[PDB]
Image 1 (tube, each protein chain N blue to C red):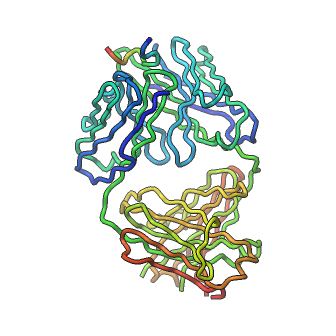
Image 2: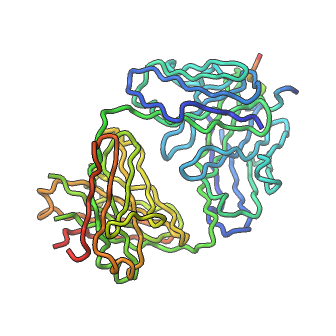
Length: 12
Length: 215
Length: 213
């Protein structure tokens, strides 16, 4: 992904 | 309602292998992380294992790291090989997760202080910092102990106001030194007795030094 | 790696004032930034995640904004509980990185240090080492300079310092400097002096002793 480390509950 | 515990041996000699473990007691997407903080410095990320099994390490730790997760015991652990003094830090376990409603949490553990040095455990010598001849200052010099930490109180705890216990300095000998001071009404120097209670638990040394005016 | 640059290094404010903290990332991280608070002796504590969401129970006076590279933490009206070190962290891509930290300290009136000099104990001399200690007590701001003079000669490379955390009651700092000499070198000189400069002093304060009191 473009932001692979982001926790799943973060972002849209 | 989540609780963190961490454990592991904290006193190491150079080239040994640090091994810490972290357990969680009390959620489905989780993010186990290790962070370390050398004394007086900022945070340095170590590594993460997440609930998908992604495993990543700080590149500056140069393939000395092993991360592992026993998912039966819920135990996240860290191995760091060939340690030098540069790895002396408090090591934190952090358990990031979100709950049944997409609220995010990241409790950190209490930390394990790990000291990497060739020095050997040694209790301190305690020397008086004697008041000069309306406010007077006096203290205790806690010299040449290893490792951290030391605790100091004054008069078995009856004296707290105006006490300053300073961060230790690490001497080129590899031993720590520390001073603890209290300012006090000079009107009390002829009647009030001042005692610093030093406890260096790593060596089970415990010293009670009386600090008097000089002459 | 993604480098996070926080600013300022230190923010000096009093309760009731607004505090703005910055964290700029070296490349776009979308909104995947978190802010932590750390007090002395404690683990960091999560405040904001995903740039803008408070963690449960974090007071509403804490607000986070930003997306892309520029992020801002705002404490709209400081409480005494808020003074601490603030870190940002990015979770766009591995390795996870932190800013260097911003220290949020209480601004108080300037207080010049009270200076005290302590000669080495008779007992430490029996051991063969002399530690001369100089104390700078209860001053503000934190910047203070200590200069050692042995027989009126400027000293270098033979002293170590440390400074306490900001006092909970009077919001000052204290400093302890140790000059270490061998016993022999200590007895080869007479005058021992601790010289202090600080924003609260219009000229240096010197405290001294002559060995043999």
